[PDB]
């Protein structure tokens, strides 16, 4: 138990840190941003959402 | 909450300040001015008002 050293390092997880990013301004009404928590929903095909 | 600084300045609105402007004098009866509150109404086509 005490005479055996460690077996190295194993990768645990690559996280996906979700802190809010900055904003740029295009003055274009079709450019939208979620200020705070939320995601847009986008459908590959028009019929099936 | 407290370790994060601000994100800059965002344009709020360009207002349209409506305080009365000064008047010039032409001594011509066809030149009109609205002293106080109100607008003239002008129509592009004579038939449609």
Image (cartoon, coloured by chain):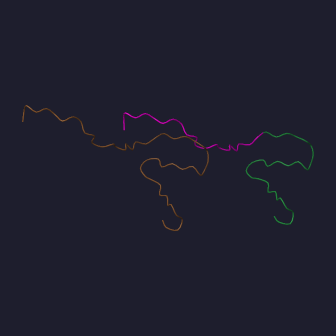
Chain colours: A brown, B green
Q: Residue at coordinates 48% horizontally, 39% vertically from top-left?
A: A22
- Looking at this rendering, what residue extends furthest in the bottom direction? A47
The majority secondary structure of the magenta stretch comes to loop
Specify whether residue B18 is painted magenta. Answer: yes
Q: What is the magenta range?
A: B1-21
Relative to residue A38, is residue A15 drawn left or right? left
Between A26 and B1, which is closer to the camera in this rendering? A26
Viewer-nearest residue: A44 or B10: A44
Question: Measured from the top left, where is residue A33 in percent x and y?
Answer: 51, 48
Q: Tell which of A42 and B42 is nearer to you.
A: A42
Going 36% across and 38% down the picture, which residue do you hit?
B1
Return the residue found at the far right.
B28
Q: Is A6 positioned to the left or the right of B43 in the image?
A: left
A28 or A48: which is nearer to us? A48
Instruction: Measuring from the top left, give residue A14's x and y in whole percent.
Output: 33, 42
* Residue B4 covered by magenta stretch: yes
Please say if A20 is above or below B49.
above
* Residue A25 in picture, x, y percent from top left: 57, 41
At 49% from the left edge and 67% from the top edge, which residue is drawn?
Answer: A48
The quarter of the image holding the N terminus of chain A is top left
Vertical placement of B46 versus A18: above or below? below
- So how many labels did they put on this image? 0
Instruction: Judge whether B29 appears above or below B10 on screen.
Output: below
Quadrant of the rendered structure where residue A18 is? top left
> Image point 16% across, 34% down: which residue?
A6
């Amino acid at each position: 138990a005490k005479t055996t050293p460690g077996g190295g390092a194993q990768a645990s997880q690559v996280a996906q840190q979700f802190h809010e990013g900055s904003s740029i301004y295009t003055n274009n009404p079709m450019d939208l941003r979620v200020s705070g928590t939320g995601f847009f929903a986008v459908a590959k095909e028009r019929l099936t959402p």
